[PDB]
Image (cartoon, rainbow over all chains, first blue to last red):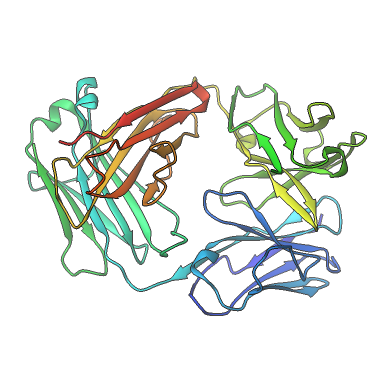
Length: 211
Length: 216
């Protein structure tokens, strides 16, 4: 079976730049190669067929090239919307096969997170549980740290973090951190603190409520 | 509109079989081969096989030989893929799609979970700051969708209307149960002088839930 391999595994480029994605086939596939673009929370979309044929509708900045065993997708001027996983596949011989994908991200100006904190709902509190939630929204770069404090003391167990994919409009990231405790640990403290560490500030961004 | 409709989700016991459906409309069903593909997170696509709706003619990936069988129903204009002897290796998103150079189209994909575990509806908790006027010119509201199985859930705000400034975070599995949250950001001119309501569906449990965000 023909094996397809893409490079790079991942990268980030600035809007406007030229980007080059490569795809190697373990044996000759002439020009029977397609490129698919799979944006976050979406189904894949055909960009290029027959190695170099722009699918109807595709913006001109996307040009496919190559033959035999080596193939290239070039984006002449990346746009923030071009954020995505790009896949290449050969349709020369059965079974049809695909590379492992290239994750393209967009570089943008550093951006500080909007931090917002939420106490447990009375609904949850009635069940025995208490989740405290903190949204750190639309920042860049992706690297961020969250720290939870209870009456001044860092809490460690019971926290769950999730990060969104990069946003196609503004190129930022968002994160959610939920601290979960029992009802009767929660009531037994007053001050709840969400503490964000990001390269945009030398001091952490703190958000906090009492009660 | 050209459409290839697949069920959102399917939960199935390991060792059992399942019939994935892909229901076609908007074009002449019998004039295009239907391709089935498998997608696991952080993997590339795997091609399962293809079937000609005109006659039922098929081509399979040898790898899926004992695993997948492709059929078609011309009167329902529906393609089906049967998966047998299911194992955890089978849990993945499955897509049907048409691969023509002048006509390339993909279903939404069905999320297959094979698990002995029983289905658990989500708890959904409104996230209010709350109070008022804090802070900047807009407000961030949210919903915590907790303790469910299996994936997926779908979260909308004001039934789709509010698509601006929504962030829905990827579910995380914490102990045989998933949790996710979603936040929305709106000018304080709307809220709370308007309904802001998160809508949550859990296909597997047929759960539908609306939680209005109430101040404080």
